[PDB]
RNA sequence: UAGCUAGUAGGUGGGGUAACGGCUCACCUAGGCGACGAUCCCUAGCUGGUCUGAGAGGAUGACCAGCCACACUGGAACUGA
RNA sequence: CCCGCAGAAGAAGCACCGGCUAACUCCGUGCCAGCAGCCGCGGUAAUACGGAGGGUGCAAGCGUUAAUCGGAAUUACUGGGCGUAAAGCGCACGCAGGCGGUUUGUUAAGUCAGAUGUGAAAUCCCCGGGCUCAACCUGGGAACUGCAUCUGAUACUGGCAA
């Protein structure tokens, strides 16, 4: 383009909306949850995986996946949600926070201790 | 139509050097003879002469040392659609000073060195490789 | 009025004053007209640590400025010589 | 004493009547630490012979690159297919800063410190032969002096 | 801070004597060089370029016994100053008080020199210096006061010091367990095994 | 001396009133082009001397009324 | 978001401020602004600076300084330099 | 801030170990149990899932997330592109803009020199001083990349006349 074309109209950027409609740029929010679900993965892999529907305090309704081994979620309880996305299941972009608020942690886990939030035993 | 003869003959000599000619002819003006004088005093071009009153024209002859060309590259930086202006400290140094720079000053047109001792800023014309 | 007060910029438990001329109604270390000198109370064995410009303060006294107690004691301590 | 070091290796295919049959390729540069740097390219059936073939071919295509002290004199451009490169002297210290598939071809040149960067798409096969002709276009003051007065 | 671990593990992993054990029998039964310990450390690991850089960084770090943050700040300060970066960095690092105490010969290892420093022993200009992060200035005096006098450790260190090379830039002195600092050391006296440029290249990325 | 500016009328005539425009070049802070720029004032005059399309200088003085703050002194190249 | 604006733009005479002033009054003119963004919408206190990148830039206005506008929500003044 | 008391005492954790990127071997699980940032790994031999032992990286902290910039030459001025990929209007004709052949004088509006006033003090930077060492405080310079005025320069554009 020629310089006159620019001085008539300047260049334009891109908004580049982020991947978390959780919005407010807040790393963590609080929810209450309503029920439990199980759904199939996509083609190249196959297993059973657990998710949960959470009705947050901002009027948003989204679904999050729960990692670990076992859980203690039923009806409604208080949990913490963090950033992060799971590529396999279509329609989830959140990870539940293990070992905080009300979601109790896993048992007997020894390797990779910091995550999953369980009181590390000192013997 | 035509918009500048300076760019015209710069492109002409570049293409002539690429095609390995031995003579280039074009009309003349005071700017042309000044730039030719500066180039010849520095020494890229062999010589020049003028002929004709009502339709004067310049002739230039290139320079060779062996089959490799002499004028490695050339381009006009100032365009009739966008001007350039530099202060004393802003005289650019092409090819780490090995090359040359054509600068038009208040005192005339000469190399960058004499401008630097005189400390005068002006116009920029072309970059010779 | 126009006075000559004291202001500090140092860290906790380590003062460092800077004598300046400004308006009375302004803050301690805020708006000021022009710096004139400084004083280091803790100082050291080194001689430096007490400097002024007698000419400017004399001019400002001529224009109609007043004095504070500590700066008056300081200038009496130094004067041209004491 | 000449130096050498491998850069990259990848497989290929032909898919002839019987099925897929393979072969391997290698590329390598050489340098004596005082300029005069060449490269080679060859293919064979297996890597241990492929690299040997590449090095034995690499002895050809020698060039002569003028160098000053330990840094390159003036900037230089470089273009080939779809890659472009840029360089700058940065006299003394700071070592050499450059991207991958560029470090080796410059290291054997002998320059102990230089600054450079490559533009655009950077497939290693194409990127090489850019610094080569870039150094080929280089001029030291003696040559330009040899055509203009002093 | 500090390492607090099996030192000859790092001696063996690096592949060269690290001068940090410094007993009397500098012999094989102590070290077992060229083994690269671990479960199956017999295999050659086939280093890469980034690995070469990281290993050189590990060697230069462990030889002088410093953590990471201090090293990064040292590189920042060296780069801020004029001159060649690598030489300036090595000269600056050499100026640490513990290293010059070791080189004077009042100890056997740098770590024990630091242990001596932390316990209020070394004396300068009639004033105690607490920490080994101190930067010595040209034309200073290193000495030991009388509370730590008549300790056999310093005498043993003095007797075993002569096996080293007594670098020229520092005056050996030690007539009455007293010394004198002269100038900044330079490239010639220090060992030529260390390659400066690679560290700078590593921090480039 | 007294600072002056030169301009062009391109304006109708009200009772004791003319409008003037002035021009000057400037370097754009981004692309380096030079673009003509126009600014407009209002003037208080005397005896409505000047006419449409005339060149006249100008100088500032006490604020007289809204948007009217400059007055003329001399007129050069009378008429077109 | 393509046409906006009658005390709106000037002139004449009176009244009111520390002062010129459509700051207000009665009269006379037919105007002023606009494609080099007027009116109309959504959004935000402003700088010396901060962060980042080599430079150009790009986001940002936390504390410390400078200046404004604000004291339950709407409006008025007395008093006083 | 100094001096004294037998006193090893009273004091270490956290991530990773297929490529991207430093470091691996066994047992149980066997499209279930599951990870993961992209490639994707799992049906009987997992250097990737769970445990054990070793190794690797930082350490009074280490990992997870949220947000900003460069890697991005992926808004391209310094620095990209339009035959076949995302891209040249269906063609012409012409206001408002932009840009102009070639001489000689005049003009100082651009532009360039020199001086003056002004770009508040912190910070950013360089020589030093001090708190046992730095963090932190501070003495003197440096730039605030402009603005305005005055005196000069006339090769190139600009206004003038032939």
Image (cartoon, coloured by chain):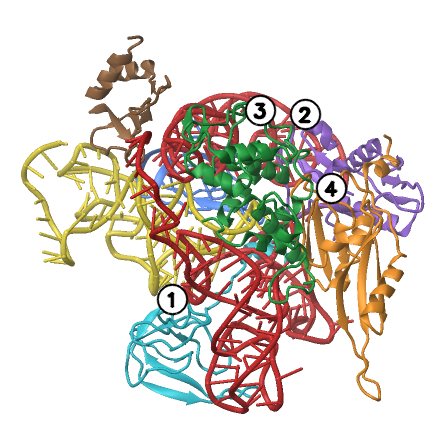
Chain colours: A cyan, B purple, C brown, D orange, E green, F blue, G yellow, H red
Mark 3 lies on residue: E173
Q: Estimate the spatial distance between the alpha carbons at disc 1 and disc 2, rounded to whole Å.
A: 63 Å
Measure the C-alpha gap from mark 1 to mark 3: 63 Å
Q: Residue at x 45, y 45 (%)?
A: F39
Whether residue B9 is visible to the viewer of this picture, yes or no, is: yes
Residue E70: x %, y % from top left: 49, 45
Q: Badge 4, how many Cα within 10 Å: few under 14, some, many 20+? A: many
Give the structural element (helix, strand or loop) at label 2.
helix
Foreground pick, C42 / H97: C42
Vertical arrangement, residue C82 with respect to residue H30, above or below: above
Which of the two residues, F52 or D23, is positioned nearer the viewer here? D23
* Label 1 sits on residue: A27
In this rendering, the label closer to the viewer, 1 or 2: 1
Q: Which quadrant: the N terminus of chain F? A: top left
Give the answer, above or below, for where E107 lies relative to B18: above
Q: Which one is closest to the eye, mark 1 or mark 3?
A: 3
Which type of secondary structure does the marked residue at label 3 adopt? loop
Circle on res. B118: 2
Q: Which residue is mark 4?
A: D71
């Amino acid at each position: 383009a020629t310089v006159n074309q620019l001085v008539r109209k300047p260049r334009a950027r891109k908004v580049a909306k982020s991947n978390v409609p959780a919005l407010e740029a807040c790393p963590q929010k609080r929810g209450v949850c309503t029920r439990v679900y199980t759904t199939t993965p996509k083609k190249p892999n196959s297993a059973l995986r657990k998710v949960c529907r959470v009705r947050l305090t901002n009027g948003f309704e989204v679904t999050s996946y729960i990692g670990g081994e076992g859980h203690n979620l039923q009806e409604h309880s208080v949990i913490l949600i963090r950033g992060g996305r799971v590529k396999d299941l279509p329609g989830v972009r959140y990870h539940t926070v293990r070992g905080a608020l009300d979601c109790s942690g896993v048992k007997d886990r020894k390797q990779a201790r910091s995550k999953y939030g369980v009181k590390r035993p000192k013997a | 139509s035509m918009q500048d003869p300076i760019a015209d003959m710069l492109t002409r000599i570049r293409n002539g050097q690429a095609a390995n000619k031995a003579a280039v002819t074009m009309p003349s003006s005071k700017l042309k003879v000044a730039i030719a004088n500066v180039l010849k005093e520095e020494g890229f071009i062999e010589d020049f002469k003028v002929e004709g009153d009502t339709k004067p024209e310049l002739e230039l002859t290139l320079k060779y040392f062996q089959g490799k060309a002499v004028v490695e590259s050339i381009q006009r930086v100032s365009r009739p659609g966008l001007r350039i202006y530099k202060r004393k400290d802003e005289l650019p140094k092409v090819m780490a000073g090995l090359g040359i720079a054509v600068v038009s000053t208040s005192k005339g047109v000469m190399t960058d060195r004499a401008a630097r001792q005189a400390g005068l800023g002006g116009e920029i014309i072309c970059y010779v490789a | 009025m126009v006075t000559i007060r004291l202001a500090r910029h140092g860290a906790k438990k380590r003062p460092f004053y800077q004598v300046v001329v400004a308006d009375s109604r302004n803050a301690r270390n805020g708006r000021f007209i022009e710096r004139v000198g400084f004083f280091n109370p803790i100082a050291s064995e080194k001689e430096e640590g007490t400097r002024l410009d007698l000419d400017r303060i004399a001019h400002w006294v001529g224009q109609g400025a007043t004095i504070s107690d500590r700066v008056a004691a300081l200038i009496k301590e130094v004067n041209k010589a004491a | 004493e000449l130096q050498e070091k491998l850069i990259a290796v990848n497989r290929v295919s032909k898919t002839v009547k019987g099925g897929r049959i393979f072969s391997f390729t290698a590329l390598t540069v050489v340098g004596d630490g005082n300029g005069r740097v060449g490269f080679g390219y060859g293919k064979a059936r297996e890597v241990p012979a492929a690299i040997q073939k590449a090095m034995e071919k690499a002895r050809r295509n020698m060039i002569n690159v003028a160098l000053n002290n330990g840094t390159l004199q003036h900037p230089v451009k470089g273009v080939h297919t779809g890659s472009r490169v840029f360089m700058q002297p940065a006299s003394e210290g700071t070592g050499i800063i450059a991207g991958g598939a560029m470090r080796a071809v410059l290291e054997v040149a002998g320059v102990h410190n230089v600054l450079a960067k490559a533009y655009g798409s950077t497939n290693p096969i194409n990127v090489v032969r850019a610094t080569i002709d870039g150094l080929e276009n280089m001029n030291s003051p003696e040559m330009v002096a040899a055509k203009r007065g002093k | 801070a500090r390492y607090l671990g099996p030192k000859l593990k790092l001696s063996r992993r690096e592949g060269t004597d690290l001068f940090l054990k410094s007993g009397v029998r500098a012999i094989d039964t102590k070290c077992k060089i060229e083994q690269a310990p671990g479960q199956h450390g017999a295999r050659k690991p086939r280093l890469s370029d980034y690995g070469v850089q990281l290993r050189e960084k590990q060697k230069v770090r462990r030889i002088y016994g410093v953590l990471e943050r201090q090293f990064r700040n040292y590189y920042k300060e060296a780069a801020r100053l004029k001159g060649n970066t690598g030489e300036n960095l090595l000269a600056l690092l050499e100026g640490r008080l513990d290293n010059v105490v070791y080189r004077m010969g009042f100890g056997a290892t740098r770590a024990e020199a630091r242990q001596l420093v932390s316990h209020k022993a070394i004396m300068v200009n009639g004033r105690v210096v607490n920490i080994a992060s101190y930067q010595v200035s040209p034309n200073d005096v290193v000495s030991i006061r009388e509370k730590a006098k008549k300790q056999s450790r310093v005498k043993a260190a003095l007797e075993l010091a002569e096996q080293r090379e007594k670098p020229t830039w520092l005056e050996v002195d030690a007539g009455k367990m007293e010394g004198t600092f002269k100038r900044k050391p330079e490239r010639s006296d220090l060992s030529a095994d260390i390659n400066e440029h690679l560290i700078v290249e590593l921090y480039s990325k | 001396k007294i600072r002056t500016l030169q301009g062009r009328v391109v304006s109708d005539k009200m009772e004791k009133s003319i409008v003037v425009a002035i021009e000057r070049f400037v370097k754009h802070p981004i692309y380096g082009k030079f673009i003509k720029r126009t600014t407009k004032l209002h003037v208080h005059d005397e005896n409505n001397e000047c006419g449409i399309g005339d060149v006249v200088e100008i100088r500032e003085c006490r604020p007289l009324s809204k948007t009217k703050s400059w007055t003329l002194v001399r007129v050069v190249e009378k008429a077109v």
